[PDB]
Image 1 (cartoon, chains in turn yellow, green):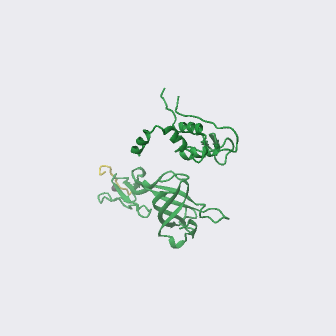
Image 2: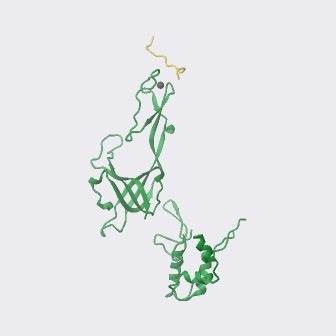
Amino acid sequence: SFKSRALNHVKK
Amino acid sequence: KGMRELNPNDIDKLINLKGLVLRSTPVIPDMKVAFFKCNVCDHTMAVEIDRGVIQEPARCERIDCNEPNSMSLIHNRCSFADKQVIKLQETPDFVPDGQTPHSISLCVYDELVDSCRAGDRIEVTGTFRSIPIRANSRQRVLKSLYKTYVDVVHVKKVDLAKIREVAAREDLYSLLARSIAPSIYELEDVKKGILLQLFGGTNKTFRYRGDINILLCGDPSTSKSQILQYVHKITPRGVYTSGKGSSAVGLTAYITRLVLESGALV
Ligand SMILES: [Zn+2]
């Protein structure tokens, strides 16, 4: 697995 | 005080200048409040411009987002003041006889934009200012002597009862005709004709127009030149010229550098 982060639009 | 007399003690004082406007820029938008938007969360914040510097937020304001480097500038949602630069030439009244006139660039803002136009002789009251200028745009490095300009805060250039009473007179035609040039000995039908030319006819929509046109001939060494000068002084927006050549003013419209110039007739 690759070190990564989920960036989310619903908190706009 | 003279434009030629300014010196570095003035560099923050409120001064007064007189001179001639050569030209002005179009209005230059000057940013007063930057408008930033977050790329991730679309939150927006306004930042006042301080001393000409954008105080960019390094991280998004919202603590529930707080992403770094994610704010971006939305140029056409910023708030802009109006700036204009005007070039003011030293008036020939003040110059020493053996050298060129100086000039000073002046910055003028908001509703003081377009207070004057090319050819206007004016006064200005303004703070004398100076700022450094760069050696090259890709570097911070500044030249060791500053541009000077004046940052202006004020600018200035350089009835019916009697009308109806006089309009009742019977001798009015002769009275007004003699009054156009009473220094000139009697040529009274010429004076009457030129008065009627000053009044003029009427226009109509459909072209037929209100212009009246007059010519004086006969011997050269006589009052006709003075007569032209007097009507020129009387008329609100007329001109004086002669039939050929151009001492930087000529009769016909003319294409030159590319620009169209309007002649004395126009
Ligand atoms: Zn954000």
